[PDB]
Length: 58
RNA sequence: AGCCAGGAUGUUGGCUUAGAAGCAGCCAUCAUUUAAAGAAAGCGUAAUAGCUCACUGGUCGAGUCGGCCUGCGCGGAAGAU
Ligand SMILES: [Mg+2]
Image (tube, rainbow, N blue to C red; front, side, top):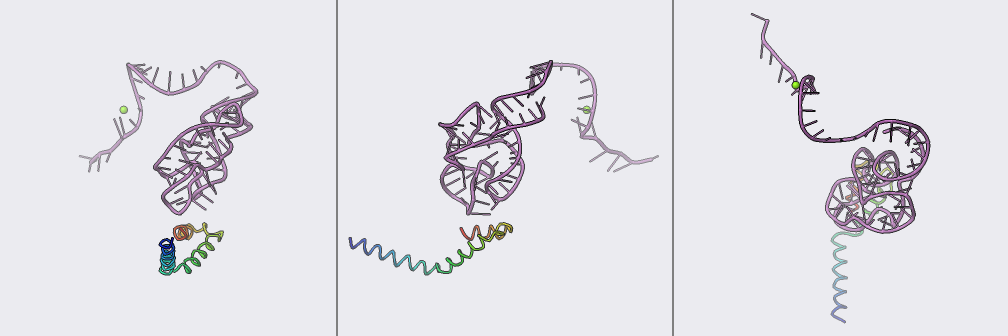
């Protein structure tokens, strides 16, 4: 049981560290603002901005 | 032929895609509601949407369709006294 217990904890550390490297906080806000621009009804009035957020949001 | 109705459902078949809804493709392509309606033939939408069509009903009432052999013609076909 304990080998797996440590397995989960190791993954905990790795996943939190990867959230650190990729800075999940700013991605969360940036994607949420991406979704803000996405909800913005004119989002597809400008195709360039729309597809920008398409690729960006993806 | 026109003309008038319908042109459905699961279901946007899924996946890759950013989106992909019949209609970018990949990719299956069935079953159901049936008069009949394609997991779509074209147009179209960023995507949907939307629009026709195939299919089918109803009014009209004699032809209509598109290949084969063959005769004669048409376009392709601009030059310098
Ligand atoms: Mg000739």
